[PDB]
Length: 272
Ligand SMILES: OC[C@H](O)CNc1ncnc2[nH]c(-c3ccccc3)c(-c3ccccc3)c12
Image (cartoon, protein in one colour):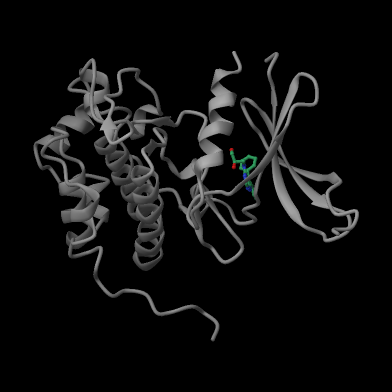
């Protein structure tokens, strides 16, 4: 009943990569655009079999949609919601950040996605600007579930024990503790993302006692960069998010009650 509408032709590369490359795949009938992550299994299929598996669970407006996959011998093809805006990373001006009302809006949408994930028992484990993509109307989408894992199954939480992620975004308990809860770790990395969006710079290489920028934060020296660029309201949120003890760290329900989070800043859509 559907025409010749599923032959995928590779228009252009959208970039690398690490695991391989991403291409813009159009269908030559509908001109229906999707993105195609191509990975060389030659270059342990558990990293990608789980990535497909987790991707099949996901169905949210702030999470990159999964459309299917392709074996084709030794090369896996992941077909994925195309985000024509690129990465949130490219909207952040070094040393400046972005307008606070844009940052707030991206933050709202990130929380919306992370609540969704945590509600279906999935933790992303690598939230950073590079993995947050933007669609045609500048809506934010969580992307890349290659490090993601189930932390809750049949209403039973599992502790995480392997260290992963990206050092500037990683929470301190994952470098200190053998085992630790998944959700506070995600929350922490959203804190670092917010800091990057409002200041255009990352506060520290890693959240260790051997890191003076990090010790400066525990000591409340908010007269230093990047904190001096921020503004008292979002900074007060950041003081709740970037709390070393994960049991004292603010939870998402409480972030939605925060004063900056609920501050009117930005007028409705440019059109209509
Ligand atoms: O990693 C799992 C992602 O879902 C696959 N990547 C994408 N997926 C879905 N939509 C996308 N638009 C992009 C993209 C668009 C415009 C400019 C730059 C990037 C990319 C992209 C591709 C290659 C590298 C980095 C970013 C991308």
